[PDB]
Length: 66
Length: 66
Picture: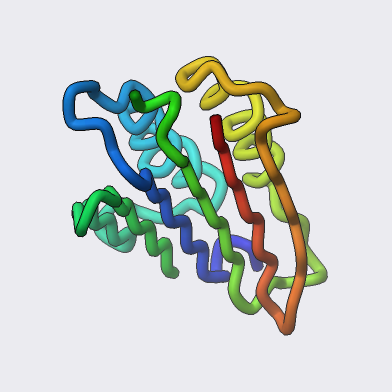
């Protein structure tokens, strides 16, 4: 099923302005943690989230497994 | 600024059950087209969206530029 399937979502902000603040990730965080969870019925324990900034790119990696 | 920055979001469903129907993408579609657009103030003309299924993986690629 879709729930049993693997859902991977990666968000990259390339050349990120440090003078400004991403006002879109906070929403995506809810979108990936809360919203998608209800669709696949997978716990935040079974969901891996890793936000990491390399070079000038901020990468947010989602791995939802079941 | 964050708006001027490049936002790339890729959604992959690996080993996709064809007997079932993704009931999470429809929401993500609104999340990437409508919701994020308001945060970066970028038009759907300046946003590239490509959904393509290869092997058993359905990939949805987002490129928001400005």
